[PDB]
Image (cartoon, rainbow over all chains, first blue to last red; front, side):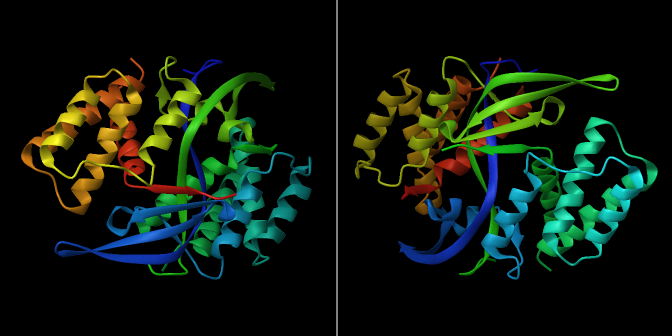
Length: 165
Length: 165
């Protein structure tokens, strides 16, 4: 489909924080607006509450926790053990860690391996499990929200982000 | 749903440009990757071509044209004629202009009026028409792509973006 010079709409997914809610009466009804901190404070976006179709993320994670997860999934230079066993054992340790950032590394590495060379049976089952742990650490206590979240995270996992300002 | 302190995933939609396509052979198959210029050159994202589910945008518009349209739709300080007739006549002129930026102003103003106070019958029909012109100026020569594009533009229209770096 794509060729050099093509312009597309890219969804730069990221963490946003509700810093304020504005209530207005427009005659003669109540209207609520979210004031969002997005891009780590570089941008304020104000959006109607009823037109805010965004997946929520747990408070223990927060804006910084969520942006960190995105950074991990989008990390371009990864170091993966070449040998299956060393790699499997390391990811096993990561899934048992309780650190969402390490779970993200597993999800990232395995999604990329899947599209690149394909997964072994155990690796495929590991990916199914890691994705579910990651979503579980992030999503609000909903199955539709978890599906959307899983898609967003999977797409991020495939992306290498290079920052140059 | 939402309250202050809540963290969400915000899709910061924007223009991306395919600057390069990388071809790789991973034994022993061909794999294509897009090298995207996103955030006006602040970020490079590299994504597998087969996993790039992005709406394309016409070349006459381009990356700068597309980002401009987003800026217009997200403009927070708008000046709209209070009187219905003055407002209607101005938007009529804009829809006949051939300038996609002016069409964007109509789409923006009417989406916001709709959620705020509601539209008159003529204004509602104007919005239906403006959205279709805007999509037509942007989309590739597909009805699924136009639907997604229309949703993206509508969501942008409702958003006030404040830049503070």
